[PDB]
Image (cartoon, rainbow over all chains, first blue to last red; front, side, top):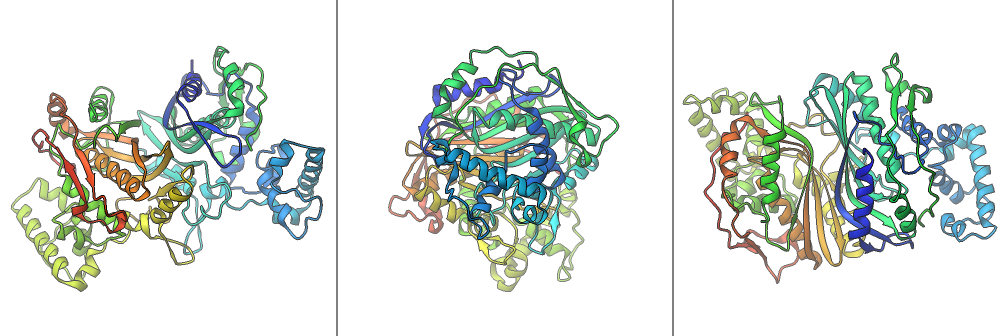
Length: 316
Length: 316
């Protein structure tokens, strides 16, 4: 079935992973070097062996596509995936004077009542970014994140490069380019960044009127992250083919370090005893073709019938 | 045998390649998305089914490692692999006034006597870069090429980043980093470059005291280029393990577009009827461990016994 490359990836890390230490006190089993291929004409690769919230993928990807780096857009769509990087900065300012909250995730996981302390400070930071304009400008903007490295890469001469907008032009004029590459890795920035881009680089390829994309992901959390990763880039591939008037081909997912955190072994073993359903179907608005102006409403998933969600500990 | 992933790559492009147009009037058969893995403890992957000149790989890689962008070093080692990019620029200057030589390779392949005209202008440019210092500074320096994007990436603040030297420090202090990445792709430069880097990005990984490297190559010429590509990065992997005091693991080769030019089909079919020999053995100087100061003399290949070289038309 279409998601089978993901269950073979998870099964291979179980059989052959190296127990490896990492940043987090949670350990991992990992491999280095892996590739998976999904043929997007056979169906959209959103996992049916576990319920994955597509609306978070769909809103986070439009945020990227709009060139946006401000949390407010996401919080407006009720997407909280990036709230911690921005909350983190609220907490070091000489403006924040509440409970101490240091390396918040760690203490909020082995949580005292500190979890709802963390969760009320966060509820407060989130509301302030929604309604307070100058607060949103100051603390809601992450600055260096995929919206801006895709669409507004900074030059040494001080202007900006819309790499995604120019590669879409090169695909419409020069489909056979072996140079349709978008990079999110910038050597200058990467020492001071907190999370240097996990989705380091991607490449488009056109052949026989079909568009494929290859992603190079330098680090991947197999249970929690990769099911989102898959669907975000299979949806980028669909969107750029819409705009360019091409059929969709394959999404090829290449990995550097792919890892399973040790406290996700039971959950992934259980997911592995489930049997793939028939894959969902993406529907993109046939009358809008400028994907940078797309809206939530413009992408539909039809027939997604998944198994239950599987609750797992986030690694810290 | 160790080189078998390369003969399976060539055989797969023969069976499944898409005939694809490209820049050159020579056409290609290509695929998109491929990975190959070579275990460097089993032997050095220099192809034995065709004689590959290791001394060109060894001198070109030290040029990169030294941070060098000047042809003179290569010409001094009798390596002419990069002479055309620099000759190309000699030819547009208001200093060159000889025969016209425009897009030289094309006319020198379907060559009149113009080949030895091209070849005497080149013999002249090459000698001038060897002995004339200010000419070498002006026309021998390529400027943006792997020595400088590995070792002297330019910032917007105007200094330089030695990405390779800092990633070797991060491996010695933080071997478990999922961030040991060197990028040769720079969005700023890549529109004006003539040949934007083919070896776009690489990543190191350490586990159980063994160092692996993964290369992402956006475009690969299977008959002529990839046998060099393989051996240059398997030698980078050996050199960084020497300097870091690690054992060598694997070299993983990931491909975006891999292509066989149409006028190399007979030659690769013939190479494919040859049987792999036992692979050579690399010997690195045991008493020098700063690889940036290595010299030709410091790397030995023992037991390389290959089949004959296979002459093929370069694509234009």
